[PDB]
Amino acid sequence: PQAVVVGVMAGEGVQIGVLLDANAPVSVMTDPLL
Amino acid sequence: QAVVVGVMAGEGVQIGVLLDANAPVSVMTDPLL
Image (cartoon, rainbow over all chains, first blue to last red; front, top):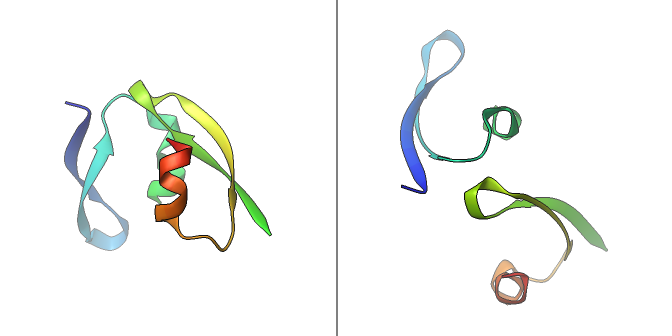
């Protein structure tokens, strides 16, 4: 339960499967995720 | 040479740490923990 796997959609349509931290606040992840 | 990075830990708590530039990750992940 410490992490969750989700599909992130990016420019023009590429879908990428990623394992994100389930409890950190969302504003902390958008930059390195990009 | 050195570097400083934001190391995330339990429940997402943000922590800042200073690490060496040339030593490999394996020799530092233990003392860092």
